[PDB]
Length: 52
Length: 188
Image (cartoon, rainbow over all chains, first blue to last red; front, top):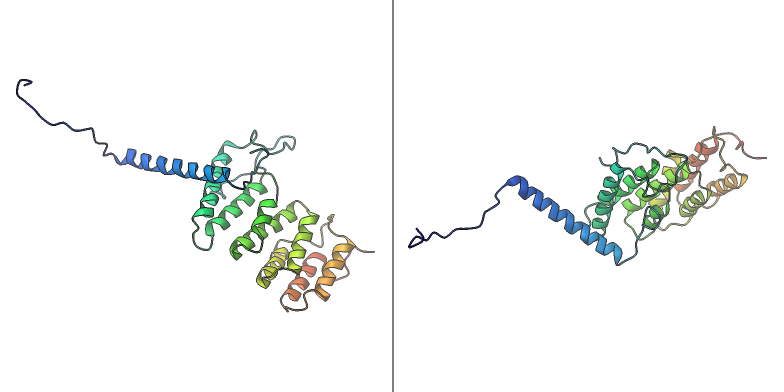
């Protein structure tokens, strides 16, 4: 085959509903955590506990 | 639903509520209500429902031994420039705090807010909530049963609420709930 046979090949597609739900959920949770920590650090802040 | 799951914490020797004694269950709840309240500060909803629900849940966590019993957050949400649903939720939390912690200065804060607030519906609602969840009843011996408080509430019935006809009936209801139909007992 190597002498004259060519087939294109693609990357492995992840079409799984479980891991797609997990990816979208974790990315949404991480971006909202990053956003709220950035907005609490660059403004006036409160803290339920001391030095928090 | 997150606020309904909160059971009272197992404080040992009145240990000060810190991050060292934070329940592993309540840390997840507290992270979620912090995320929800902060996201409401940037993207609001309708009726500020999530602000009202998160203030109610922080008061639930404070009613058990999880968050320190501090009314400063609710006192900042009960200022004039906020939406009226946030204001009445925060004032409900302050009324519950001054019932449980027997706070004198919080009761004077609430009575001052009854006397001079711009919105009269908020004044009527503070008198209503302080009637429904009173800081003491007539049967209770409390530290807040001075002659000074009897004189303040009699001055609030007599003068002070003379301009509304609904604040005066609310002050009559509050005096009835606190001191009853006879002479205030805690008096010379």
